Image (tube, rainbow, N blue to C red):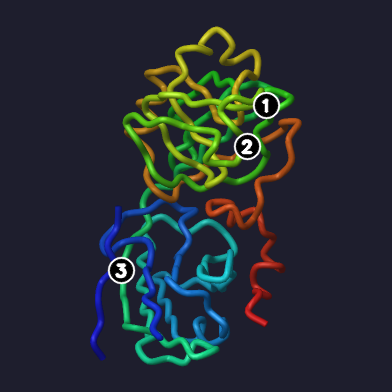
């Protein structure tokens, strides 16, 4: 066995996440992405060994043809150590593709951090280990561009970026379009939901939905969120007029019910 360690923040290479040594929130799934479509999912799954301490049952579910996820039924317990061994060098992955190499990661679970945005109150309340530490008035998506309900996993964080609607196939020039500079942006869905600084809606925050989907908070609440949250923490959205965040968004994993997840989709 030749093995490489994951980094954090013909043949197919696997890329595994989270990165070696990282500390992640309780909603962080193990993710393995290949750089080629995988014909034999059962075989990919087979080559991947996951060990947890304390041990917990878990299962694989694919989000697309090159990316598989693994998580338990419930959010991880703070302190859990997770080792992932992706033993795919030379494994037959279907239709004449094989694993280029083995990859490995070890990571741990940090504090339980769950922020719930309730559209009835327009408050985003942040809970650390079950205690309320922050209450943020928020302004979520307006009725015609609502914020989906559901469990979102915190992904990347950016001190400043531009959010551009054309990335999701909505032209900047159209009624729902935008090309917006924002501060203290914490990503929570691949479909473009962030918690981020919105000084332009402080009057509305706590009262009225005015965004395109994102969770607008005040500049200093956004900075606080950005400073205190990590990959894998949970934002839960409730009681909006929207639908439910898709299970296969990229950070929507926890919206798929356990039965459906467990049973998998390897064929």
Q: Is residue 70 visible?
A: no
Is 221 situated left or right of 46 in this image? Answer: left
Give the residue pinned by disc 1: 119
Circle 2 SS class = strand
Give the residue pinned by disc 3: 106
Circle 3 SS class = strand
The number of callouts visible is 3
Q: Are dots 2 and 1 in contact, CB under 8 Å?
A: yes
The one nearer the camera, 233 or 36, is: 36
Q: Quadrant of the N terminus?
A: bottom left
Check the image and report above or below for 258 versus 49: above
Circle 2 crowding by C-alpha within 10 Å: few under 14, some 14–19, many from 20: many
Circle 1 crowding by C-alpha within 10 Å: few under 14, some 14–19, many from 20: many
Check the image and report above or below for 247 versus 104: above
The one nearer the camera, 36 or 22, is: 36
Circle 1 SS class = loop
Q: On the image, which quarter does residue 8 sit in? A: bottom left
Q: CA distance from mark 2 to mark 1?
A: 8 Å
Check the image and report above or below for 120 versus 10: above
Q: Earlier in the sequence, mark 2 or mark 3?
A: 3
Q: CA distance from mark 2 to mark 3?
A: 30 Å
């Amino acid at each position: 066995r030749y093995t490489l360690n994951a980094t954090a923040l013909h043949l197919t290479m696997p890329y595994v996440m989270p990165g070696d040594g990282e500390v992640v929130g309780v909603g962080e799934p193990v993710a393995i992405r290949f750089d080629e479509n995988i014909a034999d999912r059962g075989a990919a799954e087979k080559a991947i060994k996951i060990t947890t301490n304390p041990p917990v049952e878990g299962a694989f579910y694919w989000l697309n043809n090159r990316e598989v996820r693994w998580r338990p039924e419930h959010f991880w317990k703070p302190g859990t150590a997770v080792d992932v061994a992706v033993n795919t060098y030379g494994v037959d992955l279907g239709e004449g593709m094989f694993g280029e190499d083995n990859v490995q990661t070890h990571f741990t679970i940090g504090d339980e951090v769950i922020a719930t945005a309730d559209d009835n109150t327009k408050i985003l309340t942040v809970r650390v280990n079950g205690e309320v530490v922050k209450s943020m008035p928020t302004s979520m998506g307006k009725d015609s561009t609502p914020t989906a309900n559901g469990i979102y996993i915190v992904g990347s964080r950016y001190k400043h970026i531009i959010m551009d609607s054309s990335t999701y196939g909505v032209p900047v020039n159209s009624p729902n379009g935008y090309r917006t500079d924002v501060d203290w942006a914490t990503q929570i869905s691949y479909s473009g939901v962030f918690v981020h600084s919105a000084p332009w809606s402080v009057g509305a925050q706590g009262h009225t939905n005015t965004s395109h989907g994102a969770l607008n908070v005040s500049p200093s609440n956004a900075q606080w969120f950005y400073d205190h949250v990590k990959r894998g923490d949970i934002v839960e959205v409730v009681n909006t007029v929207g639908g439910t965040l898709p299970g296969i968004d990229g950070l929507g994993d926890w919206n798929i019910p356990w039965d459906q997840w467990r049973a998998g989709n390897a064929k």
